[PDB]
Length: 187
DNA sequence: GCTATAAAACGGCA
DNA sequence: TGCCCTTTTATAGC
Image (cartoon, rainbow, N blue to C red; front, side, top):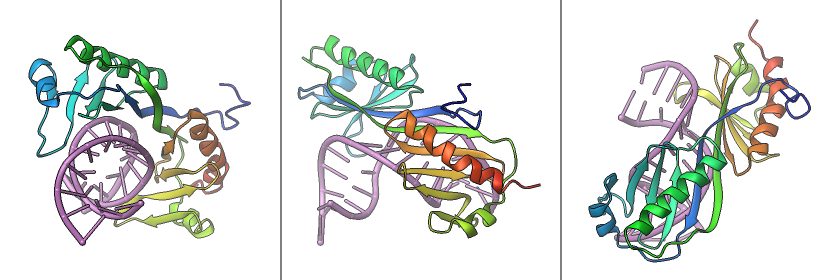
């Protein structure tokens, strides 16, 4: 571990990435679901073809406007890789698709501080940022302002970090919360 | 299954 | 632009 970028000694592992791209050509969704072997399309349920690939394990939402959403990947490069796989699938069906304005939209990470946490003590001295409602959700919601990231903190010490467009905001958010968590370590 | 968190796309409706 | 709509993922309590 590079202790200069992770003073805690723990690196959060990315669990999910959402990315968008414009193939920049209108697509016949009804025909794409008929020809492709792993595609579903219920326009009454959602106005998109839902298509999945095996490597990398992802799910794509393909719209008639030509826009595409890619979910499920574990790295930004995997998300871009999967997105180009879906785009070529559309090209082999006859559509003049491109790869315009690819952009990572959301990054989900998680980690484990490996000690129990007193959530209500945390909520009391960080009330301006936190929301703890154990009968609605068993985890404390921490809305970090700098960088703007939301963290879900649980009694077991497991952490969920979401809202990042760059993986460094994920890391900085965890490093800002780590000394607070150890301060509320359940002894 | 629900409850909560972030994000995008589209279609329907005030 | 707001609300809803779906997909993905860790987490966990009902």
